[PDB]
Amino acid sequence: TGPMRVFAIGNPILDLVAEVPSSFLDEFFLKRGDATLATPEQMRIYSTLDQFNPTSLPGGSALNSVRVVQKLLRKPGSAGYMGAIGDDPRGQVLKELCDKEGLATRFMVAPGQSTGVCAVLINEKERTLCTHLGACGSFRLPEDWTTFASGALIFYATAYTLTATPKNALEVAGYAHGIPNAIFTLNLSAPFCVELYKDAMQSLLLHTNILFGNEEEFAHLAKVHNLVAAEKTALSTANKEHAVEVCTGALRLLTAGQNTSATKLVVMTRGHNPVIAAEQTADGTVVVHEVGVPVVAAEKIVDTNGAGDAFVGGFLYALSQGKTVKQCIMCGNACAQDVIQHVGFSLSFTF
Ligand SMILES: CSc1ncnc2c1ncn2[C@@H]1O[C@H](CO)[C@@H](O)[C@H]1O
Ligand SMILES: CSc1ncnc2c1ncn2[C@@H]1O[C@H](CO)[C@@H](O)[C@H]1O
Ligand SMILES: [Cl-]
Ligand code: NA
Ligand code: NA
């Protein structure tokens, strides 16, 4: 029963994992290896998936990250989460899976809508995702969320939550803004979030303490907000120099040129390359961090999906333990490394 160390909002989704024939991907016009939102002609994909013996597992980006936090903290209610679900069987299945892990949650029910669902299709060593948000889009942060989250100083939201309404993440970040030890953290989530919610994200970033994102997301952020010269907008982030310039430019979106005692940090994951981060220190000087990623044979990599969510989960767990920025990144790396070496988006039992 607490204490709650991290509170997050997200799109609660039930992942349906199953191996399928290539004719399946072809029949539903899917391209192997891509993650997309279900099209009108793919609405029967979930019911059709049933004939392939699907495994139901809790999903959703933010939910995956807080489950990592909860697993590491162990005490029931160590992490809290809010999102919306439907009034269907699938919603009950998701809620049960979360309760047994000890996560503190409050799922808002949307009558008549279906709980978020993601088809994780395994074919030819690749993962193809097809997501249908459903009820997730109806989520509206309840007025008493601060009471539900009592005690937590670390708040987290994915840019994916902007698809319901950017007001949810703005309200959470607004609560943390100005309070020196209150930390709001955000994930860029996907390239389309950066473009589609340009202005809402710009405002949200001013209220952000820590920003997480991968290379592709940051490249889009840099282009939309003109963080670097047009001549550099296409340079490879696999180049330390360019990655650092992008991170340093993005940091300005959080600092607005001002300096307080509050945390202001941008973290860029770069696949197998070292994680790069730009941090505004106590006196306002900017310091760059480079944390190498432990090598892992390509033969031991099962799937990179979920690595990002696990990384964030680890980072936040470490942060709640008061670890340094480098230590937080290393923990995120350890969690990400565990998840990519086996089926599923959760940490191994033995971890
Ligand atoms: C706004 S679209 C969206 N929002 C939040 N999470 C998403 C979305 N699409 C897929 N997922 C989740 O990504 C997890 C793997 O990273 C998978 O668990 C999958 O459920
Ligand atoms: C050979 S590919 C590879 N090798 C080792 N680790 C990987 C790799 N790809 C991703 N990671 C880990 O996932 C984090 C980003 O989610 C990355 O920051 C990193 O921690
Ligand atoms: Cl999410
Ligand atoms: Na500072
Ligand atoms: Na995995």
Image (cartoon, grey):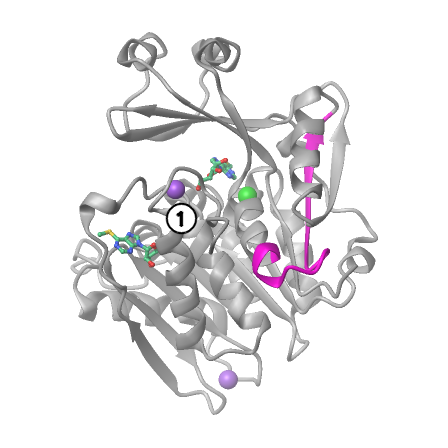
Given the image, on which type of amino acid does mark 1 rest?
Val
Q: Is residue 83 magenta?
A: yes
Placement of 293 over or under 61, stated as above or below: below
Residue pictured at 43% horizontal, 66% vertical: 331
Residue 113 makes an appearance in the image: no
The verdict on residue 155 being magenta is: no
Task: Please give left or right for residue 18 compared with residue 275 in the image.
Answer: right
Nearer to me, 97 or 243: 97
Front position in the image: 239 or 226 = 239
Counting from the top left corner in percent of width and height, residue 197 is at 49, 45
Where residue 199 sits in the image (x, y, percent)? 50, 51
Q: Is mark 1 within 8 Å of ligand 5?
A: yes
Label 1 secondary element: helix
Rendered position, 147 above or below 91: below
- Report crowding for label 1: few under 14, some 14 to 19, many 20 or more residues within 10 A (C-alpha): many
Q: Nearer the viewer, residue 207 or 345?
A: 345
Q: Residue 204: which quarter of the image? A: bottom right
Which residues are the magenta region? 70-86
Q: Is residue 65 left or right of residue 24?
A: right
Farthest residue, direction bottom: 283
In depth, the one of 270 and 217 nearer the eye is 270
At 72% from the left and 56% from the top, the residue drawn is: 76
- The spot of residue 226 in percent (x, y) is 32, 59
Question: Which residue is depicted at the point 33% across and 7% down?
Answer: 27
Residue 246 appears at what percent x and percent y?
Answer: 29, 65
In the displayed orientation, state which residue is furthest to the front: 350
Judging by the rendered image, the residue that carries numbered circle 1 is 339
Q: Is residue 166 visible?
A: yes
Q: Quadrant of the N terminus?
A: bottom right
Compared to 225, does 112 lie above or below?
above
